[PDB]
Image (cartoon, rainbow, N blue to C red; front, side, top):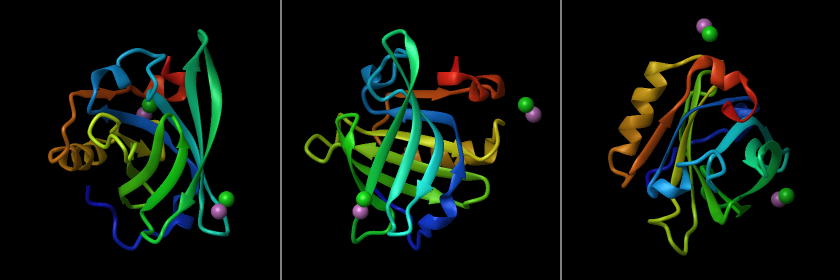
Length: 159
Ligand SMILES: [Cl-]
Ligand SMILES: [Cl-]
Ligand SMILES: [Y+3]
Ligand SMILES: [Y+3]
């Protein structure tokens, strides 16, 4: 997977909304309780170059807040995690002020664990960001794609 060259991770800080998401396995994203159905609400880069990912997940019939610490690697756009049965976070592209495309995978099973998201800065459908999302997904073996309306973006767990 091609990741972003020259990522300045400090510029991704602040509020984001999960506008769209895709996975290689349908079961990873199908239900609301599906293991990779996650909603990014905030990205908090640390001064040491790591990424605190704040997100929402639907578990036990209710919406819960999760925090994931993504550890920096030699490659600026590739981070290490230990959550959601994934071990990697990969930023594909961002303009910092509008959109951000990122993926998650488990390196042991890189085929069946892939989930990617289109994040936007405002709770609006951004078609230009969705075009770039789909252009990035072309070379990826996705079998499920989800997108959300502006009202869903502002609701807890995209209800
Ligand atoms: Cl740390
Ligand atoms: Cl709106
Ligand atoms: Y660290
Ligand atoms: Y509007």
